[PDB]
Image (cartoon, rainbow, N blue to C red; front, side):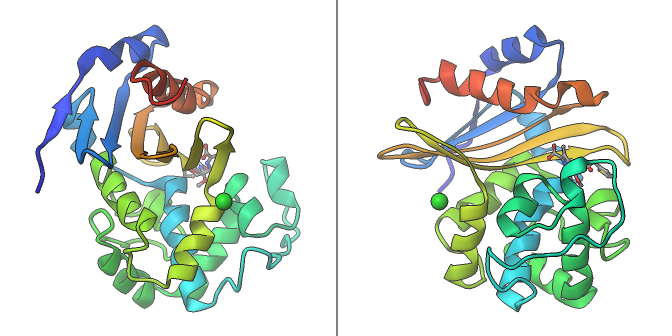
Length: 245
Ligand SMILES: *C(=O)[C@](NC(=O)Cc1cccs1)(OC)[C@@H]1N=C(C(=O)O)C(=C)CS1
Ligand SMILES: [Cl-]
């Protein structure tokens, strides 16, 4: 059961408007239909970078590295570039502000053996954790494409990943990004800088009253000045398709 990714190059106007290039992939859950502006880049695999916080949190929770979304992970004292990293954090706040050292410690505690076994169970990307156990999603060998992200998120939404239902619900809670009377967005941003090409990520889904639209976008990010375009371009596509007002 798969009809195919229906191409819609109309969305490229939003990329060129902001002098950007990239891909947006949408998936209508109720109708089982996928749509993208660039079928090739939709299957192009990249480093997941901070979007790896979704599987990392799941494993850490299911193994007991993280007890719940309230456990405090104390700042190790090292002053870092991002100001919000230099405080204590919980799972909600570590995901919101994308606190790498918190998740690097998660990976070290998970272990290379369990990280590989768990990502194979998740069917996540190329399932290659080669590199440092606490940095392989930043400069190692793991690659995931936008369509593979949607595939992974769909299983997470339906509690179908091979971790406990509780772990999956906690992560989906920590993914909450926006909510109003019209929609709910559960998503994770991402930014890959070490290995070329430099790209920005945004993967997640839009919850409506009677449907859910999964999305996974990436775009060339030569400078950090356009990080806001990850969400801005994604929403412009969502508004054009009448998914959000
Ligand atoms: C996750 O993507 C994030 N990105 C970076 O720190 C960029 C890199 C540094 C070394 C290799 S990639 O941490 C891994 C966080 N990402 C975001 C985001 O937009 O999601 C941030 C703005 C904070 S750093
Ligand atoms: Cl929630």
